[PDB]
Image (cartoon, rainbow, N blue to C red; front, top):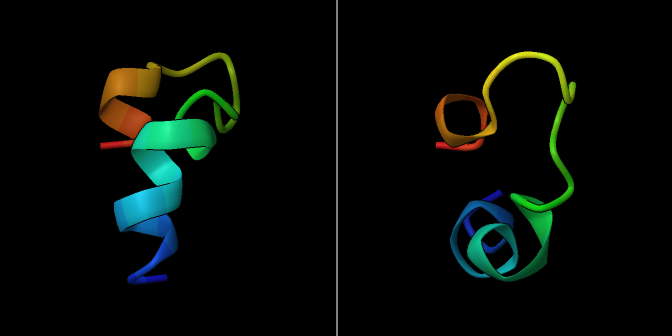
Length: 29
């Protein structure tokens, strides 16, 4: 969790786009 929501999130996993409908800036904060 610590590694994913630091290093993975900005690089590849905030462009995953969780849900797609509700807002990705607020949903992958």
